[PDB]
Length: 66
DNA sequence: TGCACAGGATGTATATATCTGACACGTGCCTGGAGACTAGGGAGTAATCCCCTTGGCGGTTAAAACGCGGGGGACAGCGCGTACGTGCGTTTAAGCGGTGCTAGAGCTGTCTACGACCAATTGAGCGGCCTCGGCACCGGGATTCTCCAGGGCG
Image (cartoon, rainbow, N blue to C red):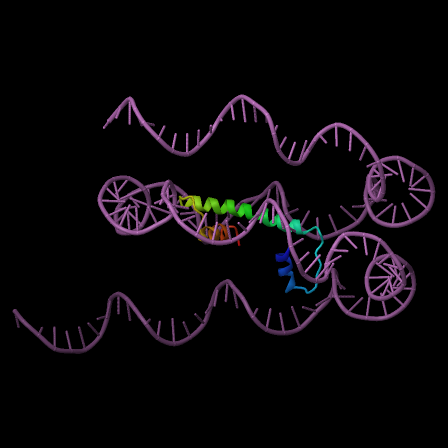
């Protein structure tokens, strides 16, 4: 909540957030980040180890078109 | 006899007339520009009510935060060999110049189904409600499932 409000502070001052639509942002963030951890996990498996590394997130990130 | 020369017999860049390709300029028929009528869709206001805040004490709990052991897994070093990198000659086949066709692509009347536009009914679908049987959470108990210590075995 305080994070979304923090991001909304410097955009439009004195806004209001409904009781809904926050669980949609958090839900999409969680569901997307889990898939990102799966693709990054596979990227770490391609290097033949059990550890996720900072370069793995960049590999699995940029390789998705970002 | 050994030798230099005067001129023909071939090359070769050099300069001139010649062949595509693309920019530049002059039209006239389907576009735009513009003028007037209708009107319903957009700008503006009057309550409203309704969930959303204001400010901060305490008490307590569950979650967040820190701290150390070490175990295993990331990771550097190094030798091997076979799997492509590199280099030849030999072949099959695309590029391209040119040809005879056609069958499907492409612009144009007819009318005729056939869907756009508009009254009248209603009933099937939406706001409101209030229950109970499926659901939430956990005990009881059996079951599996992994962790650690010999020891019989190297």
